[PDB]
Amino acid sequence: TLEQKARIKIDSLNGFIAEVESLGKDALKEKLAVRTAEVFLKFANWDENNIEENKSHFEKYWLYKNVATQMAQELPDFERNDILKMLDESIAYIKKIKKEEVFRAPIPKVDWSKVTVGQDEITMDNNKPVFLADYTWKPDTPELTEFYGELNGFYISPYYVTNASGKINQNVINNLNTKASGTPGFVFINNKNVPQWAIDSYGADFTKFQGAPFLDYDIDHPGAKVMMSHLLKGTVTKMKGKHYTDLGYMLCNEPRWITYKDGTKKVWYTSGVSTYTLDKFKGWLQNKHQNIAQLNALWHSSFSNFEEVVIEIPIDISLMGTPKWYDWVTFNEDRVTDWFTWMKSELRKYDPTAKAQLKIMPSFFTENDPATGIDLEALTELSEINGNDVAANYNYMVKGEIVKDEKYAFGWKELYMGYDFLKSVQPNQLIFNSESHLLSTNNARDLYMDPKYPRAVYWAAHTLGLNASQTWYWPRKEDGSLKSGITGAYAGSNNQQPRVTNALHATMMDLNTHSELIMKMQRERKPIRVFYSKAAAANKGSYMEGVFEMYEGLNFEGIPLGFATKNIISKQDSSLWDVIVVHKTEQVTLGELNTLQDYIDNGGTVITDAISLKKNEYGLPLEGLKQTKGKLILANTVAQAKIEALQILETKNHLPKVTVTETNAEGYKGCTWRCVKNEQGNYVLSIVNLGKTEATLNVQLKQAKNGTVAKDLLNGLKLPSQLVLKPYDVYLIELIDE
């Protein structure tokens, strides 16, 4: 039987591990293989005995609905055979280790008990930087914490305020009194299960208006603060300085305040707003317009004063582009930011050192979701840790079928644009993906997913700033059964994927081995900033297609990309970059325009196309920019702006000191790369093939005295002049002058 073969493989592998370590080499990756094999052998025996439960889970996901029986029946032998391939791959490699056909540096073993969470790095002893990985709901057992992480945490919810005097649930106080510091983790603030006293006191209106589906109450109702203050006051002083606050206080799980309509189509999570919200909107309208006639001309309204302003919320999406749509969506962003400005300062009263963060989805930003109320920049400014749960799309499920990315190996835009924006707003802060959806999500899933994919995307995520991650997800219990509450997200995901799970932590050991090189790419200057306007975004649903168009054209030059905004220019040192590129940003506020002028007035360079920067948020004409002491370069096409932008770096001497030229059968580059200098002063490249076909790379130094010879840092060999990259392939190489 397959399991009997597998235990034979395990026996041979363990034997090889022992021999290699006796010769003084490191076999920690292969030890991860064996454990992953043991664990999933257990998973598969439970599957075999629970076809009916597994069939019901496969019925919950549309891709597998019609073959649920088939999938549940075949799952145990899928997992077992995946385990065999895993053991074979490891057995072969540990023989190359034994025979010295490869040289792999000892992998550091991350003891979570001996790691320190800094401002922009996590480090273990010896001050070696490290990167942390765990899973959502993984069991806390020795079997799993040895390789799959030891993330700590604490969970609070307004349901713990048991009366209106602010008494906290006693079993929670007992737990908080006896829970030790423990390993590093984060505080989860639930915003559901409003307690009965709040309902009784504040009435039906208190929960009629929601930040659905993860906040169940009216953030603008005065009771909202009374309730949240009670919870924070009664628990947080017990948490101050505990290691389970090291990765912050998560103020909200996937926040959003969706407030638009679409005729008779169902808009998920949308809500109206209370009288309290309209009262703040009126105040906001007073500050924005000054007098009612100005608002009335833009709204085509005829209010006599601001107290008489009326707006229908949810506001229909057909109004997008109108002044009234801009005012609502912008105010909605601001009022949500106000709630978290309040929530943070209340938190600080009880833990003055608290690091705020949110589990924000950056896809609202990269996909330009309408009327969400989420100002990604403004909530990231208020955070000490760059929280998020960004995703990537191995595929796209359309109407219950798999569709692949039309252009690349997988959908990476959300990760690269997302994290580059996070690291432009908070360049000196850690990234903590507290519910990583790089493996699977609502519309991305494949039981048979190629194990090269988790490697590429987690490697990519870490070059971009990722420092710690809780990966979605590990719903399996200790004995291999499943937690109750299994939804459609389960079928096909990582708890049915031995080699996908193996790849993840095996890629983490590569990342940790060479973590100093990764931190150099995370800290690298970002000389080119693509401009982003919330005003353009509010007005044009398709706005982020033109933005990605510019970003995409720049993202394969060995340069880490960044963004610029009004606040980034107003608040940060312009010497941190060389040029700002504007592309297809047709509407901006006057504050945005003048800040871009201030940047040129003080010696900066702006590349823009002719169509941008000439209408305001209401569609009224703006003067655009002028060249003064700095420079203004006009360039309509992505190709021209790319030529102009790279020249500015050339002048300022900020181009990579390495060139990479790529052949592929696609007509565009798909190998994205990074270049930094190591301690011996040799240049090191990280390369990921994002393209859907094989790429040949000619890599050369710029000042080579003898030549350019590349060495594989992962396995210690010299590589051929023409590097070949299959889709998803990952290279970490050092360039030598020979």
Image: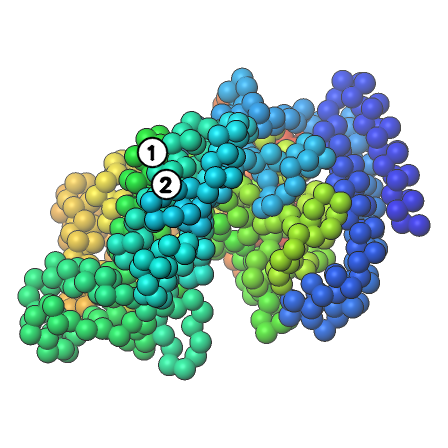
Image quarter of residue 90: top right
**Amino acid on which the number 1 mark rests in the picture:** Tyr
**Circle 1 crowding by C-alpha within 10 Å: few under 14, some 14–19, many from 20:** some
Badge 1 element: loop
Q: Is residue 157 left or right of residue 637?
A: right
Q: Which mark is residue 380?
A: none
Viewer-proximal residue among 611 and 720: 611
Q: Earlier in the sequence, mark 2 or mark 1?
A: 2
Badge 2 element: helix
Residue at image location 72% in from the left, 57% down from the top: 448
Q: Is residue 56 left or right of residue 514?
A: right
Viewer-proximal residue among 69 and 171: 171
State if disc 1 and disc 2 touch (CB < 8 Å): yes
Q: Which mark is residue 350?
A: 1
The residue that label 2 is drawn on is 232
Is residue 448 visible in this depiction of the protein?
yes
Viewer-proximal residue among 524 and 462: 462
Viewer-proximal residue among 599 and 645: 599
Image quarter of residue 601: top left
Residue at image location 51% in from the left, 20% down from the top: 127
Position in image of residue 346 (x %, y %) = 30, 40
* CA separation in Å, label 2 and label 1: 7 Å
**Amino acid on which the number 2 mark rests in the picture:** Leu
Position in image of residue 637 (x %, y %) = 35, 61
Position in image of residue 358 (x %, y %) = 41, 46
Task: Name above or below for residue 624 compared with residue 606.
Answer: below
Residue at image location 73% in from the left, 51% down from the top: 481
